[PDB]
Image (spheres, coloured by chain):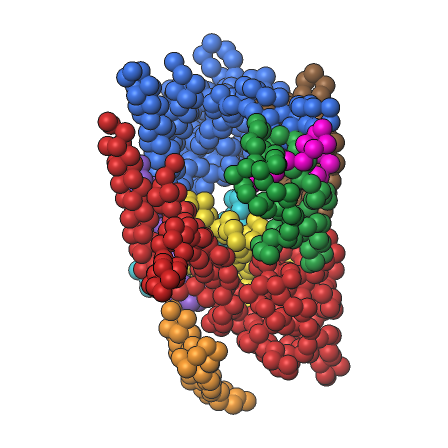
Chain colours: A purple, B yellow, C cyan, D orange, E red, F blue, G brown, H green
Amino acid sequence: GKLTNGALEASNVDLSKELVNMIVAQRNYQSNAQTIKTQDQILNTLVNL
Amino acid sequence: SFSQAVSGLNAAATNLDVIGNNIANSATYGFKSGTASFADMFAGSKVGLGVKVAGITQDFTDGTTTNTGRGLDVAISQNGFFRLVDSNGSVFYSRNGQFK
Amino acid sequence: SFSQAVSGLNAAATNLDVIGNNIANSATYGFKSGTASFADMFAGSKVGLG
Amino acid sequence: SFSQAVSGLNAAATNLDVIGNNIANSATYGFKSGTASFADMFAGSKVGLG
Amino acid sequence: MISSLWIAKTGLDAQQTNMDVIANNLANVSTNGFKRQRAVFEDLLYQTIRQPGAQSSEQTTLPSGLQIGTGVRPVATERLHSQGNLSQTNNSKDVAIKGQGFFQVMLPDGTSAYTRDGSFQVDQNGQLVTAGGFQVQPAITIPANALSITIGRDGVVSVTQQGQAAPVQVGQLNLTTFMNDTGLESIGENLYIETQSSGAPNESTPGLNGAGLLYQGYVETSNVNVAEELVNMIQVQRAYEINSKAVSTTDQMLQKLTQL
Amino acid sequence: MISSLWIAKTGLDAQQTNMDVIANNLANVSTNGFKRQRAVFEDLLYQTIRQPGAQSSEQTTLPSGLQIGTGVRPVATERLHSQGNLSQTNNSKDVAIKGQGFFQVMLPDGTSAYTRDGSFQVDQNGQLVTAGGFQVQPAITIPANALSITIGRDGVVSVTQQGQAAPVQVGQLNLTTFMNDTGLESIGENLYIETQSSGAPNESTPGLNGAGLLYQGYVETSNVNVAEELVNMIQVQRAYEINSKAVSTTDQMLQKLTQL
Amino acid sequence: VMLPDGTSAYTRDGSFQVDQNGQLVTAGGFQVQPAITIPANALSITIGRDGVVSVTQQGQAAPVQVGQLNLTTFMNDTGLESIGENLYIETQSSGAPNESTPGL
Amino acid sequence: VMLPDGTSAYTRDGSFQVDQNGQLVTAGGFQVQPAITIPANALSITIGRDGVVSVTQQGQAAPVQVGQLNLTTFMNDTGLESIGENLYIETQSSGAPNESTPGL
């Protein structure tokens, strides 16, 4: 590419894109973490008998 | 069933961690945002082994140039890099344009 | 995994300090403006550390 | 089902940025105004995917 | 040592398999080009104490026989090759396939596999490869000093060189369709290979013979419905608890019988 | 007194060691420069009632023998010398090491220990000592009336006095590495000493022969992640409960045997 | 794995450490048969999908192979005598082991 | 089931292993009479509902037929003389066996 004197680049990061993806990621973690809790109680019921 | 869930739990954490990294490095000059990608894994058939991280890729779309004044700076309009050398003889490639 | 946010918050607050100092010290004859500079870090895996 | 909301936000953001680009490039001699055009998507069954 | 105990054990195993497939589906909800799994069972054999419709006398027949089940058996955990939502990424080296078909990939050992997730990179040699080092079967090679890479609606792919005032075609991405898409056995890293269940694959250009269309800049997400995975998990948990209750009841009655 | 009871006792002991390791890892989640530890087991011997692959007849061989396990033994508890994260402490006398290597230190008796800590202070006599009273082996001293101490990316450390308009070099912070960092045995107050498992220490300036680099004003946090520790606690608790239930079943079986 | 007496055992337990000489030994002090010697001053160690094991060093801007990890299969893996510390020794019921590179 | 001395015996307990030569044998070294041989380095074995059995190779996508697993019936099962090793031997009370394919 062609150089340009007296200039600098931005971060090419869009806060609107990143913030919404953080909402989606958090729910995926909780939904996965729900499975661990469910599996623990499945084993918990079996042990107590 | 912990094996499937724990692997998925780690994958979600890694995805969240990368988002935090992309959101903290904002306003950095020579920075390209990165995203992670996953891929399932089955031992044979009908059996699931969870999910693993399939590498982290960086989007090299050029950012918007800024007229920060000064004389000892330069931004590359298109694809390209600056070649930098360390005192030990290593070679490092950078996109930032802060020179002193 | 608070290392990402706590590093970002310190950098962001420091930028406010630099901007605040520049605007506060306006109309000072022998004053030269300042500006911060950032740089990402990578210790181990490809995931950043702030 | 965050796909539709995410797609809607990105489409809305793109429209705003293009509008910002057109007003920012005012008082420029050799410039032609820009405008973004959208199009819906359908791949499932009678439900808009964004 | 009891038929009831064995039946309850089979039921517990079936519910465990159902829970495992639900957990696996929930795990990789963010995996691109992922088709969820559904497990289907069936009833096991029956012991016939009295034959149904038995000739009970010279002129009368039993309206219904006496049959006792032997439990349940999981038939298979099939994969639902549904259609996933197309996201937006605005990249240049990833294509999403809308419709039916797969991309052909040359595995290192020499055989060929088929994939549904389109996110291509370039190796150091300049040929188009997927995430994992596998190179595409038609061996599309991207030349150096490439200004941009464009992929049309059909399989034709062109690259804009430094000059020449015209893009130049570099190859074509034919995609292969199957007859029994749900019969392809799955290996890791979003790959499929053919078996006797699926017919002989037929390769074709996109948009013909029922094939899909290639959109550049998008990506195919997983078709996992987390909104209903949770309620399925609730039902699975309740069934598992009730089967455990049945096992406990059998143990109690055996104990209070042997206490004589 | 019985084989099942002894096997269950060994299993309980293994799970107790695992729980202790988890608790110790979680306790010092905020200690600077801490490297977590992981416990590794391996099963004990097997009593062979019938030799596997034995010659049962003139030509027939047993496809599989009869073997009974004796339990599980915890083979080791190894440190995981990963790379800890770094933070901004903003102290002139705080250093963090990126990569691999250790800071040498001299014990009061005379031997040498190795550490990963960075909170460097000054003794009453002006010698650079760590938190605890130990002083670095190369014997770096800080003169009085010192304005600022600057430690470069490599091992050179300089100080500035009131005048002279130029820094003066004081010493070099050479750091030592080992062939097998995992074999170092830990001792109290965040120190490591050389053993036979690890090789003879090799000393070098930072940035050469694979050694790390020094960053002034930072501090390295422990390499412990709280997310997976809780799920490990859940799993180890369930395993411990299962082993206890096995002990209970063995005791009940024996009691019903001896009730005669 | 080569036992100290001279014979060879087999294992599936993946937990590799390095002795003071840099050899890649299993957890317990037994070295792998091909004797993969990890050199010192190693910035990083990587193991590919196949048996190739490479090390990224301080310079030379290129990973260098230091060995390979082949694995041996048996005709019938059930009939393997099981000594302690996660080791198996071949018997008559299991045919002579055949070594191979991974993935083939 | 083929006894070592040459005679044939019949059993119902289905729990098979694989010998070092690939012959499908039961727990005890006795090999199945139709001589179902499994070739080496077989990915997996699939036995149909009928008497067909086939293993799968790597990079073939076509299971290979290895044999037919027939089972024999009797006029009167009660008349079989039970011996050790969980096996039955025909007698005069039960008629001669008539081997037939499964499902027919």
Residue A23 on image: x %, y %: 36, 62
Q: Quadrant of residue B62?
A: bottom right
**Where is the N terminus of chain F found, in terms of image quarters?**
top left
- Is H17 in the magenta? yes
At x 46%, y 85%, the residue is D39
Depth check: give the residue in front, F101 or F145.
Answer: F101
Answer whether residue E78 is visible to the viewer in this image: yes
- Residue B14 visible here: no
- Is E197 situated above or below H14? below
Task: Give the dominant element type of the magenta stretch: helix, strand or loop.
Answer: loop
Which one is nearer the viewer's eye here, C31 or A34?
A34
Q: In this rendering, is residue D29 above or below G1?
A: below
Look at the image and tell me in which quarter the C terminus of chain F lies.
top left
Q: Position of residue H100 (x, y in %)?
A: 64, 51
Range of magenta residues? H3-23
Which residue is pictured at 72% across the width and 65% down the height? E137
